[PDB]
Image (cartoon, rainbow, N blue to C red; front, side, top):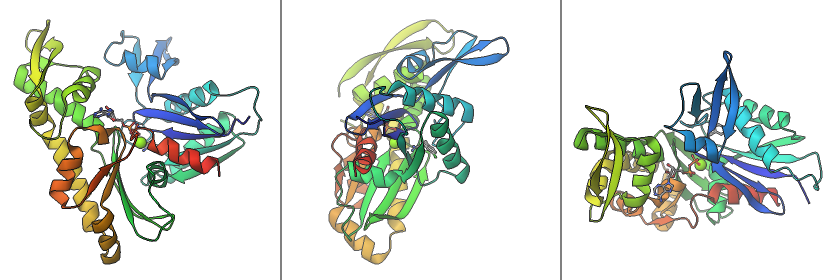
Length: 322
Ligand SMILES: Nc1ncnc2c1ncn2[C@@H]1O[C@H](COP(=O)(O)OP(=O)(O)O)[C@@H](O)[C@H]1O
Ligand SMILES: N=C(N)SCc1ccc(Cl)cc1
Ligand SMILES: [Mg+2]
């Protein structure tokens, strides 16, 4: 019975894998703060804090401290990490926990140090950082030990991370700020301009899951929100075609991120990727039809990982057990 853990500290979701157990926590990367006096106190972290997005009283706020793939607020990110690490601690298990945290290719020395220290301050005795695209690839079942290159396209909340891997190493990696959040924001902007309806970010994500698609058909759902000009609540019906229209720009920007990475690939790795194609991971990979859009624009096979939301945690989990 161990307290050793591997953490996927995602822009939108945090997962923890505990040695010998598997994934024991999976909660939004959100912290709610309450203004008391002139200071901010931690009010909630995780599932309850996400529920407060768009619903806070004046003296509270809900923050995603990793929202854009960078640490926006070190103290709030460290409180978020300490909360989750503390939450899964098993008093029956051994002390001196070894903690592995996944780190995106773009993370700075400053951010890596800050994650290291947050884990120490949360009780870790030793901290190891592992490259996130290696984690994604492993959890997606890619044979990353083989010499032939693999390309993984990991579409998260605040970023899409693209990497080419070979012989247990990363050869190329690029990050762009397009992913699940820009898809939500596109649906917000669509509803405003086309239906004069102002919607919250949690509603926008729901619309994306229920009817979002990367290609036109279709079916319809009710969407409720705030009237633009006059401010009273009302509702309108929106279709799959309309959702496709709304998502077309951020979908195109993901496709372009994939093309840019491909265009950097040297000849022998290009031959490797032209064979095996591209593996999609992250929750953004669940967008209906995104795989076909990428296939159509690249000419390459596109596969969606099993369980795309958990690939990174599963992969670093495997590393922790070995
Ligand atoms: N069924 C779905 N369709 C489209 N997008 C989805 C779906 N489920 C989750 N997502 C999106 O996936 C993103 C979360 O992906 P995730 O890999 O957890 O990101 P991160 O690792 O940065 O936290 C969010 O934008 C979420 O809305
Ligand atoms: N995990 C992501 N893809 S974004 C958050 C993050 C986590 C760790 C560091 Cl060092 C920087 C950013
Ligand atoms: Mg991620």
